[PDB]
Amino acid sequence: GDPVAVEALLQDVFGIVVDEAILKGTSASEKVCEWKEPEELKQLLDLELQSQGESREQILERCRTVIHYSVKTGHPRFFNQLFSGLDPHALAGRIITESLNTSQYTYEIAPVFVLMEEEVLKKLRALVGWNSGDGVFCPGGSISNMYAMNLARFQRYPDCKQRGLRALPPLALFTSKECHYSITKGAAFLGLGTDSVRVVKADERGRMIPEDLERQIILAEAEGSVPFLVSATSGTTVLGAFDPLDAIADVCQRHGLWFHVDAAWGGSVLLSRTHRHLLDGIQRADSVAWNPHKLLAAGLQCSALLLRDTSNLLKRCHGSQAQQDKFYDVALDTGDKVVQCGRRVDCLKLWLMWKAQGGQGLERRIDQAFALTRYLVEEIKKREGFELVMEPEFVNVCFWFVPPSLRGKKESPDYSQRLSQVAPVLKERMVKKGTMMIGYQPHGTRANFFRMVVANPILAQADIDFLLGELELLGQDL
Amino acid sequence: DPVAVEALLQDVFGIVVDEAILKGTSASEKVCEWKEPEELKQLLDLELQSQGESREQILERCRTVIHYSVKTGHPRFFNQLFSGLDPHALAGRIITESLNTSQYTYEIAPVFVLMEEEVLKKLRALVGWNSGDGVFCPGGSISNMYAMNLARFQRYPDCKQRGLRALPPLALFTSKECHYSITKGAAFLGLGTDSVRVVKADERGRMIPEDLERQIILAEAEGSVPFLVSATSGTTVLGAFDPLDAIADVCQRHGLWFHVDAAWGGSVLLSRTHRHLLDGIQRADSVAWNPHKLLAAGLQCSALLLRDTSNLLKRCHGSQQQDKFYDVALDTGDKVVQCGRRVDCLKLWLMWKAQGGQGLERRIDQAFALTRYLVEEIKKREGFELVMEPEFVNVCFWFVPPSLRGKKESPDYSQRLSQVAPVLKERMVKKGTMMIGYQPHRANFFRMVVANPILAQADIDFLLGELELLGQDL
Ligand code: NA
Ligand code: NA
């Protein structure tokens, strides 16, 4: 409780965070990762909790250690996930949130943030194209899609809330083959079962095929299942595709189906007049999942769920059966909207950055990410040994690195099997060297290829010249 | 510009220290700065615009957001089950937000992939298990939804693929003092609220094993298949603790999943004195435990522990070679249904390292002690009436105003008293001297929570003296 000791502690800890985590964490001169084999890091960390406390110095050193051996996700050469970058205003928002440590649950304990969330959700709905609606923030995009499924099930068969799924006919939902696994996880968690997820084929560019969607819908109807929801993707996690929302909307409307748009990754594109055409027709959706923590670098878990409904379907669905004595408009309380009880404050980090950058500052960051995606594509097409998997529609640049030993050997019967062995070796070498982290995955018959993500707001051409030169160095003997 | 970033955050942290941490823990300051919703909207000027704002305007927005927010760490904040500001946990939280990674793979979160297991390993130890599984979740409501789902999958693994229509009607059982997340989770998981069979609670708010087993037998007679029993070791209102060793016996006789919702009261396991309240918890299949509530770790410290050592957690929430260059068993992505997951272990681990097991024991024991002092002063003071003897740190009590003292036999005494707490709540919130919760159950009564680590007897003398002041004309 001693205030002077507390301030001195937090100020000392903040100095280590600033120097070692923020400044040194975003410097290209430092490493992205200080690799240690698990057991060696176990010993280095000395994690075992004990009965006796430790001195101030031993804790501050545990901070320096935790920072040092952690990956620097805000590094200009961190391309391993869909998120990248460390916005200082967002960080300022994050710190204020953790210090106030409240629950986004009632106006009584979170008055500022209960209103802030309403405004932010109102702006997001505007960028979607709605002048009215409902919505909530959720802990991750996976939960935003489970809400959408559940809301569709309840909107069509409200008895499900009480009698359960055994009182309903078999239900069928539809999503692209390029979806995030959160649809199949949510379907089983919601009791529908993985079989209830009918996969729709994607075209050459990774976009759902509206002709096959209805073909699936009609077949599902013929098997006894009842179509109720369609999930399009506006920014797949691998290729960065954008499903045709206006063509899928037509299909949903022709069958009176819930139209949900998983825009967790690509929904942030709606802030740029230049590239927002990629989500044309999204205003015809019933629900939209949108994670500004990915592209705008707001920090996890910035995950929103927007709804076009204006009848409190959200409260009637996730509400309970239990005030009439409180001294304020209880419409501000959002407890009946979610199935959670306590909920973090996830709007401040986004709102504060948005206040500092302005709508313009965030547009340029999106435009600046698309611009650098062109530069990366330029260098891949100009450089030998780098082969683009496909033309990128987003900031996801998928590409192989063909080492010298395989260039020209495409007609070899085992060309695929050996080329698939290249990225795993290049990934291991870059992590242990600590120079960069790039993701890679197989995609069906396609061999292990990289997946760059041009999203870090401090990225520069020099970083793309390095990672491309770095791969050439690390794969010269392959 | 590195210097601009450093100078920006350093200036922002100065505002956080003064207004949020120091002034937030000062008893001379207010707990809440009440503003009518419409006024606060205009005051805050939340509307987002095309043009950004200057550094000066941002720093001013920080102080304003802090000023009008509630001070959950104030010595006179008793509105929720959480209260207090552990500085070590706060340090961990800031380190967490700055490194901004996902508790998903050892590749991107090597330090925390190990840290979390050790913490979860210590929690399983305090439960009484030398082995098991577990993960952190975003709130205890999700910890109970996972537990429900794990039981459904463990008994009927075909459910994951074929759904609930491929299964017989399922029935779960819980006390009338359960968290409402049970009825929500049951509906969210597709079982339906009717699948939740309510069991009667005794005079102390505790589940009655005689009624539990009676319901189970009725469920079997109606065609349903009992599969799970959800006990509570620290209800949200009264602070009850179900008899875990008696319910375990019933679960044992019917081969049912025994889950213990210890989100609130699980922290008692750190005190040798008071851990007898959870005897039999080592006989559970699963246990939900939130260190953010009592220990002041900060939301969302909510764990889900398992006695299972057969990777039931991955087989249930997983997704269905890759060639990665390290033991992929370290990755915990298949354990949860989320994809990216926050790091919630550092704040607890750092505090536990600084306080030691003894320092955290000291806090729990001192919370029970201060809870007794509150009960002492309530029984000695006129106008304060205890609802029932508290077994935890939840002290439920009425305040009978002077106009109702001695009039207990009036036919409308109860109705008149139920109108007292709502007015005392409004007057304390608009005055800003303290925030105490109250709930309906006979008549609206208060629910103190002796959890703030910096609480003192002077604070208990104030809230009792303050209530008398706010209700002298009622
Ligand atoms: Na090329
Ligand atoms: Na009394």
Image: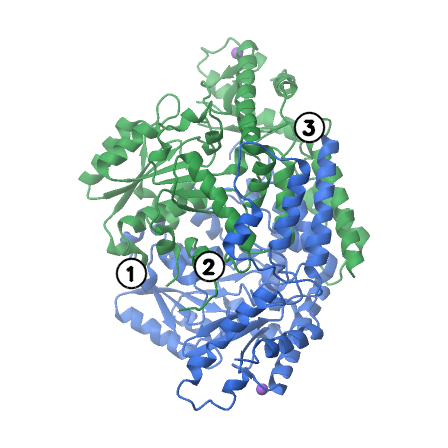
Chain colours: A blue, B green
- Classify mark 2: helix, strand or loop: helix
Report the front residue among A225 and A363. Answer: A363
Q: Where ligand 1 lies, by quadrant?
A: bottom right
Quarter containing the C terminus of chain B = top right
Mark number for residue B431? 3
Chain to which the residue tagged by mark 3 belongs: B
- The mark closer to the camera, 2 or 1, is 2
Name which residue lies at 76% across and 43% down.
B15
Q: Is mark 1 within 8 Å of ligand 1?
A: no
Q: Which residue is mark 1?
A: A170
Where B329 falls versus B388 (above or below)? below
Q: Are marks 2 and 1 on the same chain?
A: yes
Quarter containing the N terminus of chain B = bottom right
Q: Which residue is mark 2?
A: A145
Earlier in the chain: of badge 2 and badge 1, it is: 2
Residue A302 x, y percent position in the rendering: 58, 55
What is the three-letter code of the residue carrying label 1? Answer: Pro
Name which residue lies at 67% across and 34% down.
B32
* Residue A310 horizontal side relative to residue B170, left or right: right
Residue A125 placement: quadrant: bottom right
What is the three-letter code of the residue carrying label 3? Answer: Lys
Residue A131 visible at all: no
- Classify mark 1: helix, strand or loop: loop
Where A215 falls versus A168 (above or below)? below
What is the CA distance from the residue labelled 3 to the residue labelled 2?
42 Å
